[PDB]
Image (cartoon, helix red, strand yellow):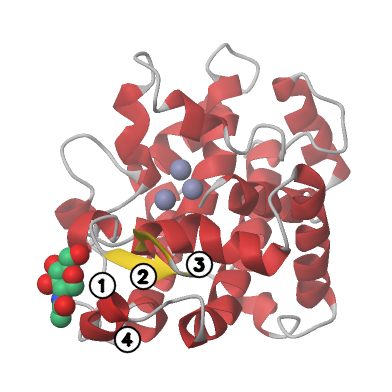
Amino acid sequence: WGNLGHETVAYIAQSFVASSTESFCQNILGDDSTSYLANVATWADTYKYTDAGEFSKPYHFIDAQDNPPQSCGVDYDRDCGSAGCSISAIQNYTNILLESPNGSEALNALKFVVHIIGDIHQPLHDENLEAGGNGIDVTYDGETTNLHHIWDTNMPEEAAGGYSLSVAKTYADLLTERIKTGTYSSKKDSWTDGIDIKDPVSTSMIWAADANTYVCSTVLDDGLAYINSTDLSGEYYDKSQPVFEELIAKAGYRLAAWLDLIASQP
Ligand SMILES: *[C@@H]1O[C@H](CO)[C@@H](O)[C@H](O)[C@H]1NC(C)=O
Ligand SMILES: [Zn+2]
Ligand SMILES: [Zn+2]
Ligand SMILES: [Zn+2]
């Protein structure tokens, strides 16, 4: 996701964590604001463009070697790769926070976890096709961009009505209410099924697999002919909105559950 997506995921999670989890995080981050997670939720996207953080670029995705829209699926060993991936990063950074939450590596670990749980839920961060769709040029609202970009940024920013922290907060609030009492409030009871703080690979793969099914059902189900030739800010946006909204909600909720586990220090 772009910044708005990551901040919305972070604010959602802030709404569901226990108060000891909040303190646990605020202490690591040195931030006692009511935006403590949101404020660090984009950091990994900065860090990967620095010389020192270049090595972390692959941690944003798992390039699923599947065949969408006909066939979707993710496999850790097949798809992660030689330089690591979202899944291996969640394992490594989760275990740092389980082993040394007060150590020097915990600050970046937590920043990573907040960001990457977000990324795992962007379906094109779980998809190899044309560099996760970065190679698929498309027209969005009369302007040229790419398919990955409109999922990261154009479409969420349109649905949220902007891109500022306060817009992310308002968006998070809307989605959090969907989880509590609205359209997600039944389904959400099963969004943490299979979660296991002692198996970060398996837990994060479930989330990645889940998000990846939407490559076939939604991202690409019209076919590349349509996608390459149609302005995607029309009916494509309308079809995609419920899906990216639910995924951002799942990301927030799952992030909170995972942070509550880490803070509980098993
Ligand atoms: C769509 O465009 C992508 C490149 O951006 C290309 O690889 C693909 O072959 C195109 N497919 C069709 C059906 O136009
Ligand atoms: Zn992202
Ligand atoms: Zn992206
Ligand atoms: Zn990212």
- Give the residue drawn at x 79%, y 66%: 176
Relative to residue 88, is residue 255 drawn left or right?
right
Label located before the other in sequence (2 or 4): 2
Residue 255 position, x and y percent, is 62, 52
Label 1 near ligand 3 (CB < 8 Å):
no
Tell me the kind of residue under disc 4: Asp
Tag on residue 73?
A: 1
| 2 and 4 marks in contact (CB < 8 Å) | no
Tell me the kind of residue under disc 2: Asn
Q: Helix, strand, or loop for circle 2? A: helix
> Which quadrant would residue 37 be assigned to in this image?
top right
Tell me the kind of residue under disc 1: Gly
Please tell me how many numbered marks the rendered image carries.
Answer: 4
Residue highlighted by disc 4: 221
Residue highlighted by disc 2: 212
Residue highlighted by disc 3: 194
Q: Helix, strand, or loop for circle 4? A: loop
How far apart are labels 3 and 1 at the CA level?
18 Å
Tell me the kind of residue under disc 3: Gly
Label located before the other in sequence (1 or 4): 1
| 1 and 4 marks in contact (CB < 8 Å) | no
